[PDB]
Amino acid sequence: GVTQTPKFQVLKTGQSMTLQCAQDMNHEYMSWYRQDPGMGLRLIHYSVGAGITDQGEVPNGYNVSRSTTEDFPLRLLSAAPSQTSVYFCASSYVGNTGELFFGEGSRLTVLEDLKNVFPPEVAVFEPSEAEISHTQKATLVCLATGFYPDHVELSWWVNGKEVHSGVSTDPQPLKEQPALNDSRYCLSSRLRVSATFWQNPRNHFRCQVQFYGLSENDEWTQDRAKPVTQIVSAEAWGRADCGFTSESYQQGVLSATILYEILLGKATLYAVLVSALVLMA
Amino acid sequence: FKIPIEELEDRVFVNCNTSITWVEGTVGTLLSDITRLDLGKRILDPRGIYRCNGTDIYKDKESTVQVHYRMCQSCVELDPATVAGIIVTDVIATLLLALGVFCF
Amino acid sequence: SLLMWITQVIQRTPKIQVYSRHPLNCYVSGFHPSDIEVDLLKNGERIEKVEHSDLSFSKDWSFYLLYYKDEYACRVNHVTLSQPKIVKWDRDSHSMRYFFTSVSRPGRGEPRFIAVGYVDDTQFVRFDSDAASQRMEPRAPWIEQEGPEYWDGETRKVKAHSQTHRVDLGTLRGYYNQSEAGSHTVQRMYGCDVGSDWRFLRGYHQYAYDGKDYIAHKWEAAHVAEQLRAYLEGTCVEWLRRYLENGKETLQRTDAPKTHMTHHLRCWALSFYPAEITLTWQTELVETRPAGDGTFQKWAAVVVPSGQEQRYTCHVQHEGLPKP
Amino acid sequence: IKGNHLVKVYDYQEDGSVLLTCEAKNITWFKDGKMIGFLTEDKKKWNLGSNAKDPRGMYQCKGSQNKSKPLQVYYRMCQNCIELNAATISGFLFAEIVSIFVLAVGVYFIA
Amino acid sequence: DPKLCYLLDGILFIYGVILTALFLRVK
Amino acid sequence: QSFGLLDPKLCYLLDGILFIYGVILTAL
Amino acid sequence: QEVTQIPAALSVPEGENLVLNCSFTDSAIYNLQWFRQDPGKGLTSLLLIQSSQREQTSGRLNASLDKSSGRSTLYIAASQPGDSATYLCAVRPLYGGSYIPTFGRGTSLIVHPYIQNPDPAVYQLRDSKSSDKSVCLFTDFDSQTNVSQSKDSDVYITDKTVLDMRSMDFKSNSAVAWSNKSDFACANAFNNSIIPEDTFFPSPESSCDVKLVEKSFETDTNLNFQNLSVIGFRILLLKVAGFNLLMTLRLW
Amino acid sequence: QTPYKVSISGTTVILTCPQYPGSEILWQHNDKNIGNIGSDEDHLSLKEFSELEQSGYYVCYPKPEDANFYLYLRARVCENCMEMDVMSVATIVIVDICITGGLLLLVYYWSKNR
Amino acid sequence: QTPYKVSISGTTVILTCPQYPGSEILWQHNDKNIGGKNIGSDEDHLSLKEFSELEQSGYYVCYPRGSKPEDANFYLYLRARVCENCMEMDVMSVATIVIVDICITGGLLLLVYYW
Ligand SMILES: *[C@@H]1O[C@H](CO)[C@@H](O[C@@H]2O[C@H](CO)[C@@H](O[C@@H]3O[C@H](CO)[C@@H](O)[C@H](O)[C@@H]3O)[C@H](O)[C@H]2NC(C)=O)[C@H](O)[C@H]1NC(C)=O
Ligand SMILES: CC(C)CCC[C@@H](C)[C@H]1CC[C@H]2[C@@H]3CC=C4C[C@@H](O)CC[C@]4(C)[C@H]3CC[C@]12C
Ligand SMILES: CC(C)CCC[C@@H](C)[C@H]1CC[C@H]2[C@@H]3CC=C4C[C@@H](O)CC[C@]4(C)[C@H]3CC[C@]12C
Ligand SMILES: *[C@@H]1O[C@H](CO)[C@@H](O)[C@H](O)[C@H]1NC(C)=O
Ligand SMILES: *[C@@H]1O[C@H](CO)[C@@H](O)[C@H](O)[C@H]1NC(C)=O
Ligand SMILES: *[C@@H]1O[C@H](CO)[C@@H](O)[C@H](O)[C@H]1NC(C)=O
Ligand SMILES: *[C@@H]1O[C@H](CO)[C@@H](O)[C@H](O)[C@H]1NC(C)=O
Ligand SMILES: *[C@@H]1O[C@H](CO)[C@@H](O)[C@H](O)[C@H]1NC(C)=O
Ligand SMILES: *[C@@H]1O[C@H](CO)[C@@H](O)[C@H](O)[C@H]1NC(C)=O
Ligand SMILES: *[C@@H]1O[C@H](CO)[C@@H](O)[C@H](O)[C@H]1NC(C)=O
Ligand SMILES: *[C@@H]1O[C@H](CO)[C@@H](O)[C@H](O)[C@H]1NC(C)=O
């Protein structure tokens, strides 16, 4: 396959950033595309052999350079607010079959200032009792609100293991104040689980949100903590709240244990009597 | 020919492209689609041999998979020191009973 | 017109001939690899304006190059020669082919790469990696009527060829378990041949590693057969009619060679435009050498005792001569 | 990672196991600075048994460099804690009084 | 569940001690 | 529903013997 | 040289055969590519048609190319909800030296799931600490109903999404609405959107069954050891009490 | 070297920072600044402890990256619930023996003698 | 079909593959060769010492030796948890042990009764 890095990046206007594209199957044709929302999949510089590079349809503002048939760097010398888009690296053979291969893509966002970025706030809401009584299924809802930009990945974890089934994620975040220009987004995710599995107190559910923010290099000056790349989590234990469960059993058996220690101590004490007393008789 | 089995939410499922044939073992239950078999709760130790056909290039070659589970739901810890202490305590108690009934 | 879509993938002693074209040229053939040194000597000094034609090779994968009271000499240096050899001087149907060669220069960043295009026996395109032009240069007198976009396409396709050859250089180096220190050459030839009524009959696609015939699995999968056959049976023949019509003034002009017989028995012919010729003596066979103007000359002998050179006859056979 | 601290804890599991995570050629663990474990390349996690035992101590992993910064692990699972609600204290008092009552009548008639 | 076992133990033992006291009373 | 050897049937297994002793003394 | 896709919008019930169309102006080509695209996650190649091939097949997906008319059609059989994505048609040339493909605009495809048993309901999730927002959940509604945005800026109402329980092959639709609001009651949260009359508004009172809870009970090993120790202590106490009673009666 | 010193009483949790004497100290919690929460005189007091959002990594520093220690505390507290190991058993049974013998002697004396 | 044989004791696991006698057996686990000091290969058995759940649960297969791994069509799927000195004891076993304890106590009591 073809790997391009980084996945996400936030740039102050005027900086320089070089995305990296690499492959190991020694393709020959390489190219860069930028995909704009609702506009099209436009082309950037393309190179067919080592040392030769040609322009596409959007050449202005970009560098490329190819000296090794395995790598392709795309450099922005002075990032501009119009550079905000998603970039793909297309790699192919020449003449073999003509098949193309695309990378996972890279998101870029250019901001006039770095004040407006925020880390997400994550909360978890437990299923209602009415839903369990009515359908015998439970629905946990994770909310990640008040972050900007939307370089966010959401995931669920159960017992320290990721979960891929029964999880629905909103594909489009909601702007908190859609009337004006950029505002913090809100995102929601849902996880449905059979009522038997949720009502077990041992099960431990976690919602994780990975957020890609400023790097340590970038200066920070505001009073609040610098919003560096991080991961925010929220947890919840399975709970019955209806009847008999394991923990009550544990507490009861332990209380009985202590009571029987006390009782046996008393009984053997008085076994000392009428045994150390009849002995002298 | 890897027979895949999944472990969704404390239940074990046998997945295949075609019908599933049961050999000696836990029968389990069939879902709405015949192609997937539910083997019950994880901690109930489902053990059995199952068989499935193939698809496409794999068509046709049989495959059989043995599912074995050992979840300690009926276990206890007892090192030799602990069990030795228990047996000595009980034996002194029983000789105490014997000495008692002798005294009567 | 090069093929755009490009599916990936013994030492011969040099032979030297020396002559002066009209009644000074040194013709070398059968030498490989291309690392040659050739020079012309003895006006007490070396020759200054030494230029050579393009580097190519015949069907046998082996090269053939040409350079063009006083006594002269020719000196030749090749790795097959422990001592540089010196040779003295004595005065007394149609087809298209494309030959591609790429040479590994251990240490140099850009390995050498040249491409040559031949119709009949005449070249019409030139491209050399080490050349400062870095574009497909025509240098031919009947191709300049084309447009610049044509040459842009040729440049792009030839650079694609260059990149492919650069890649399979290392590919075969890994395949045969060789080292980086050694220098190896890859050679490719493809073409297609037409007849008197101007339609395709034959095609060639051969590929060799350093002068060893290699192929004429990946490919099988790669579905090369139909596309390659379509290219050979397609764009060649149309373009080939096009060059033939635009090159009609030169390409087909039949030249009548002039014949001579000497004894001091040698029968010699000169200026026959196509290469194909035959000389018969009712016997040592020598390779045909050009004159530098496009016309060709050849020669053959019979050695006889004293006084009896009169009872042998040489007959010259050719497509452009009626009777031997 | 840069400031050492190469050792981390992996906690939530189906059972009560608590795992410790640290070149995949030889892993030398140190508890209170003493050799407590040698770990091969195939195995990666260092086990600590059930968390009901309240596993606590110094931990440090070492590979090819000069070990790692220490980590102090502390656990307090109230497997022995008792909810001293009204019911349990009432039961305890009732048991104590009835036991001592039967005991007292016995010893009274003995004398 | 365990509680019922324990209270049944207590009740039955109280019954037992009462019966033993009665037996000793008319022994 | 996995009791294992936490099965409550075990508990009364002891209580049962306390039962039979209790019935021995009634026939007095 | 120019590639157009028809009809750039598609919305079907599950299990319906699908025909997708891509046309190109220049017929002298050597390639054909069809790519899926989820909202993100790059492009996944589906298919490849050569200049020598009229048909191509891959699983439940089929495709044909008629070069003379310059058309290509993709046939999807028995559509599943997993096929909702954008489809792109791309072609590469035969002459020129450029090797630059010409991508089409793409066609978006959505396949609604088939709900066996509709059961629209509006539950209210219990609020968690460190949060001042309330959450109502609208779920299990028929795929024909469909929700709108809120009338006010304080209530945030997400869009309906499909959800798949692999454990017991369930398919469902969901929408979530949350807000600060002081009087944000789930009885009137869904008020821009027309929803079925038989909507189940569960009563505020809490009702539960313990029998369901008993099914999730299970055992550990430590509990087992504690129970065993209890039974042993009971045995030992019985033994001691027996000896002690006998000796007590002996003094009498 | 010197470990972290904890003290759990009811819901209250108190930590200590033996290192860096004299110098002013601050604390972290999952790599975020912290300081119900009280911090003074080289200690940290968490009141009304809750397991879920207060169990994890803690560090005390006078950059916390190269701080000379780290703690991973995971412990949920039961209010009015008191932990008891084997020696607590020893004390409770011992006082039980003492009181039952002391109350036993009086009834023995009353039944006997008089 | 001859089923796979599995034995477990403490933290020791033994796997027995009776498809082919006369040695000629070597084991594969999750696409890795295994058995070729806590892992051993016996003439009909494989021995795993210090077994773990997380990293040693999955597919196991016998080729047997002289064949290729892909030729196999009979696989073992295994996951199991073990502790230091853990025994499976069923409820009936505990019932029997309590019963025999009571019985032996009563037997000795009867023996001393007629002394
Ligand atoms: C059950 O049927 C499905 C659907 O046909 C099979 O999934 C597909 O299986 C083929 C091989 O028959 C896989 O092709 C190859 O897979 C790998 C990974 O890409 C690689 O060797 C090749 O590049 C090639 O693609 C295909 O990936 C796979 N698809 C998926 C989504 O898993 C499946 O194998 C069948 N299962 C059984 C047990 O028969
Ligand atoms: C702490 C608890 C377990 C101690 C109680 C167990 C033993 C000591 C109890 C249980 C039953 C009791 C007996 C029950 C009835 C009587 C009859 C009475 O006329 C004299 C005392 C006597 C003979 C009791 C002696 C003490 C006794 C044997
Ligand atoms: C039963 C024999 C051995 C002695 C007689 C003493 C009686 C009164 C004692 C012994 C065991 C005791 C029980 C042991 C365990 C518990 C669980 C606790 O959460 C409430 C009290 C309760 C339910 C006790 C009630 C009183 C009890 C039944
Ligand atoms: C592209 O980068 C080169 C060096 O890599 C630089 O000289 C050039 O100025 C950049 N592009 C443009 C359009 O100036
Ligand atoms: C599996 O394939 C065999 C032949 O290899 C055939 O006899 C059998 O009926 C098939 N079973 C199923 C369920 O398709
Ligand atoms: C290092 O690994 C080897 C090979 O597994 C082993 O024999 C040796 O004991 C290990 N040494 C240490 C110090 O861990
Ligand atoms: C696609 O093109 C074919 C060509 O025959 C036509 O029949 C069909 O109706 C077209 N489909 C659409 C959706 O336009
Ligand atoms: C694909 O569609 C074509 C045109 O309808 C049809 O002839 C062909 O059989 C289909 N492919 C398969 C594998 O059925
Ligand atoms: C769903 O949206 C579609 C698209 O406009 C619309 O036709 C339909 O009426 C909506 N559903 C309902 C129940 O109104
Ligand atoms: C309601 O919650 C939102 C979410 O940020 C907040 O902006 C607002 O201040 C909160 N409180 C009130 C009283 O509106
Ligand atoms: C929903 O309730 C709001 C609040 O009372 C009200 O304004 C609105 O009219 C209701 N919906 C419709 C469709 O009228």
Image (cartoon, coloured by chain):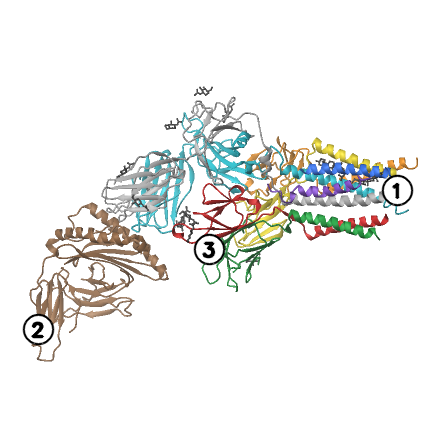
Chain colours: A cyan, B red, C brown, D yellow, E blue, F purple, H orange, I green
Label 1 CB, ligand 2: below 8 Å? yes
Q: Residues within 10 Å of mark 3 (few under 14, many from 20)?
A: some
Give the CA distance from mark 3 to mark 1. 80 Å
Which residue occupies the extreme bottom position in the image?
C306
Amino acid beneath label 2: Thr
Image x and y of residue C2, in percent: 23, 52
User: Visible in this render: residue A273?
Assistant: no
Where's ligand 4: which quadrant? top left
* Residue at x 20%, y 60% (from the top left corner): C50
Closer to the eye: label 3 or 2? 3
Left or right of G62 on screen, residue C23: left
- Quarter of the image for residue A54 reads top left
Q: Nearer the viewer, residue A78 or B47?
A: B47
Most foreground residue, E19 or A129? E19
Most foreground residue, C276 or D97: D97
Measure the C-alpha gap from mark 3 to mark 2. Answer: 83 Å
Residue G252: mark: 1
Secondary structure at numbered mark 3: loop
View extreme (right): residue: H114
Q: Which amino acid does label 1 sit on?
A: Trp
- The picture places residue C250, in percent across and down from the top left corner, at 11, 55
- Residue bearing mark 3: I73
Percent position of residue H79, x then y: 66, 33
Q: Nearer the viewer, mark 1 or mark 2?
A: 1
Which numbered disc, 3 or 1, marks the residue closer to the eye? 1
Chain assignment, label 2? C
Camera-side residue of B103 and A65: B103
Q: What secondary structure is found at the residue carrying circle 1?
A: loop
Question: Residue under circle 2?
Answer: C313
Q: How far apart are marks 1 and 2 (CA)?
A: 160 Å
The answer to whether mark 1 and mark 2 are in CB contact below 8 A is no
Residue I36: percent from the left, percent from the top? Answer: 52, 60
